[PDB]
Image (cartoon, rainbow over the protein chains, first blue to last red):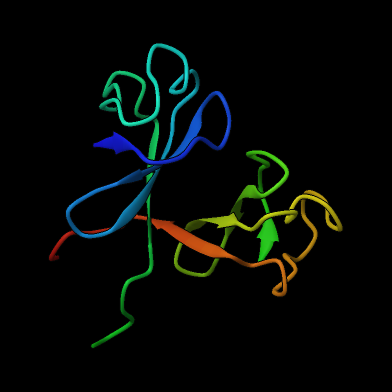
Length: 55
Length: 55
């Protein structure tokens, strides 16, 4: 899980195999940087954009 | 779509019928507040936490 963007010191826009994701972790931005792998101990909430409804 | 949390001036943690969501919109925080409906013209990216994989 890399960091494609930065929302704040906890939320960041990441990207997974499926598509773009969002990593919300208190202090996630701290101890990491853009393009760096996301720290799993800091992973508090993983969000993914709705790709498809039923299809 | 209400605003349960605020990530920055564009990203905010919202909540839909399915579960918690994330609204990433440049200026989304501006022209709105916590618990207020999210402006659709500002909606740039909607993210939802992975509820279930296959089940």
